[PDB]
Image (cartoon, coloured by chain):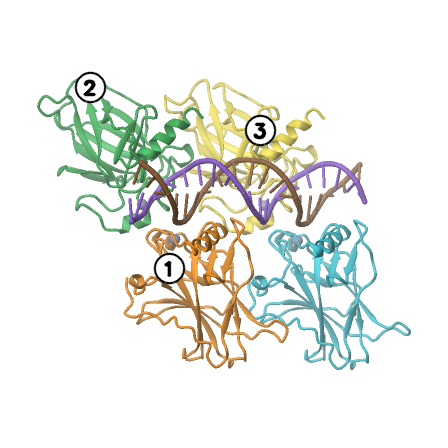
Chain colours: A green, B yellow, C cyan, D orange, E brown, F purple
DNA sequence: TCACAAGTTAGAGACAAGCCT
DNA sequence: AGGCTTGTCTCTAACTTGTGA
């Protein structure tokens, strides 16, 4: 089904200079998660760990939160809620925390919350923002994507964006960034292909 | 049956500098939607996505709406209401929102409204106007045309115009633009043919 | 919709030596009705006169009737009732005698009856059998076919057979014959094409 | 889930000399249904017409029925009930007669019955046996397969057999035959590949 | 990773079949 | 009846994208 609205995807570094960072990987055919700076696009395998770094120029207040939400990238599909396909929603691979219909999970965080928006029908996953750990310069969140982009009855080969928002305790916007995502069996192969096709 | 009047088709950019834009496609025999600047004519396949861009020089007020209506292009046919043919009206391919007789649908918009004008008998489809992200420069609406121009008992090979009007909440005119439409099996082939014939 | 059964099409000359005959026409591109002995197939234009000759070796009893019924030729379509398309059913071209949904009409016979079979849902048209007018060797019935084979939502390019049955006053079978029919804009052209393709 | 038993697949021509026949098709990459005598295997596209001929040496009694049932061909999978995948079960493409979970449908038969066996949990589809006329030599049933062999969460790339049984009015066995089935996007390509691999 | 399985898209070309000067 | 309009089919080939020894 459809949402009545479309979440904004405009980059907004905001008062805290909020930026995203990604690990440097290359393109071994079967690498588990790899980011293309050229495409601003993450290529990852289903259910595998996807590190996303949060960088700020100055620390936001205690109670700040970090939300992730997927939307379809193509305008004609933007109003359709991104969710898991009928098969994966039924295979019971929940980690005890995530509802079965949610595409994006956060792993390794007991304070994770999953939201099914009463008004927009959009799914999202939120964790408290924690400043960087000793001497590290950034905060890392580990996401999992629970369907392939290709999943019939779900994303069905349509590209998505992940929107990461920094919010205050009330849900007010503090910052926003986004990246494209392809969940696929062969992230290395597929990243290479799409990068090659930039010239075509 | 016939309407008592004919909707105006005169271009009117109005106070907000309202213009239309179209995606740049070429003419692969079986492309789904392609626009000819030379003919100001959209060539599209039945039920396929047809993106139309709304450009304004300045943002209209909240509550502004965008209406689409088809009329026959030829003067002798202008008073005839454009509607779906008897076969397609009966094939039940409604998206739950559009009445079966309406030629033009909007896809991916929960706030769509379909009007069967009590006085003029004309069909139209309207959605709220939404300003672009302050990143994008225009707003895109996705239309679907639900019969071929050739449909016997419907358009019956007669060309139509789509009239796009920008209206206030009361239905008062703020701006108007229009383009010719051919719904056909082979948009690319047909666009090429008609453009070639410009010289003939 | 579908019938629960399929009418038999087996030739049965029966006790009266019942055979069909057709006029000798050739293949002028736009001839109105032409019969191919090679294909046992009539090619005719929509609503035009199609003469069919009834030949018998001996005269059946007074009260004998002649029924015509169409069925789809292809096995997968045989259970589907042959009827007019949605457009032609609605165009009101009835001769005051034929129901609008019936494909086959008889012209020039005040004693024609149209049957919509309560059990099989099949349409048919029946007239009283009349022996040949003094000196002629056969009885001619003039049929009209009220859709093209190509009509979308009706025959939809599927070939049909016309089954002609000689019946007693109770509807018991006395004899049966059949021929394929194509209703088309250009019977002469199309007959020639199908005959040429016999070698291919 | 699993059945407690496995339907027999042993060929049994029985008292009436029950045999199957198939149409002669070749291997155009995108043909809709093609049978390989070498593999005794039908290759067909999802939801497309699959003609199966029933041949008998003598006519079974009125009330005889013809049942079709799918089972997995591989022994380790044989106890698993063959059914549609979660996606296709939910896409609502029912013809008003078939339950959404059934893989095999019969098209064009108003007397079709769909059985969900209370004890074995197996799905099957059955129609009354109808003799040919004394013109045709066989009776044809038109099946549709409503998932690809590859469907994730359903057949999941596992080959199936279709078992066709001739039964009396009580369900007692009169005859049995079977053939392998692959439902796939490119029956011609795939048939050619598997036939070539017979030598490998 | 490679080799292969198996679905989807885009051409092109050849036709199919209505229209009307 | 020619010539053209306009929908449909085959076709092949490239490509997409998952699987597994
Ligand atoms: Zn999935
Ligand atoms: Zn139509
Ligand atoms: Zn018709
Ligand atoms: Zn399926």
- The answer to which of B68 and C53 lies nearer the viewer is C53
Q: Which residue lies under the disc numbered 3?
A: B179
Q: Separation of disc 3 and disc 1 at Cα?
A: 46 Å
Q: Separation of disc 1 and disc 2 at Cα?
A: 53 Å
Q: Indicate which disc residue A16 carries.
A: 2
Is D175 situated above or below D68? below
Q: At which x and y percent is residue D175?
A: 45, 76
Circle 3 sits in a helix, a strand or a loop, which is it?
Answer: strand
Q: At which x and y percent is residue A167?
A: 21, 27
Which chain's residue wears label 2?
A
Q: Indicate which disc residue D101 carries.
A: 1
Circle 1 sits in a helix, a strand or a loop, which is it?
Answer: loop
Among all residues in the image, which is located at the extreme front? D199
Which chain's residue wears label 3?
B
Front tag of 1 and 2: 1
Is C133 situated above or below D95? below
Front tag of 3 and 1: 1
- The answer to which of A156 and B95 lies nearer the viewer is A156
Q: Are marks 3 and 1 in contact (CB under 8 Å)?
A: no
Q: At which x and y percent is residue A133?
A: 10, 25
In which quadrant of the rendered view does residue B156 lie? top right
Left or right: residue C119 compared with residue C40: left
Q: Residues within 10 Å of mark 3 (few under 14, many from 20)?
A: some
């Amino acid at each position: 089904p459809l949402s009545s609205s479309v979440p904004s995807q405009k980059t907004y570094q905001g008062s805290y200079g909020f930026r995203l960072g990604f690990l440097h990987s290359g393109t071994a055919k079967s690498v588990t998660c790899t980011y293309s700076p050229a495409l601003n696009k993450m290529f990852c395998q289903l259910a595998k760990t996807c590190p996303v770094q949060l960088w700020v120029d100055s620390t936001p207040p205690p109670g700040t939160r970090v939300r992730a939400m997927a939307i379809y990238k193509q305008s004609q599909h933007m109003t359709e809620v991104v969710r898991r396909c009928p098969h994966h929603e039924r295979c019971s691979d929940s980690d005890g925390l995530a509802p079965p219909q949610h595409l994006i999970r956060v792993e390794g965080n007991l304070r994770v919350e999953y939201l099914d928006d009463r008004n927009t029908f959009r799914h999202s996953v939120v964790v408290p923002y924690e400043p960087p750990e000793v001497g590290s310069d950034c905060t890392t969140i580990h996401y999992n994507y629970m369907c392939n982009s290709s999943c019939m009855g779900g994303m069905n080969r349509r590209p998505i964006l992940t929107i990461i928002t920094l919010e205050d305790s009330s849900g007010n916007l503090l910052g926003r960034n986004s990246f494209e995502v392809r969940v696929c069996a062969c992230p290395g192969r597929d990243r290479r292909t799409e990068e090659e096709n930039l010239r075509k």
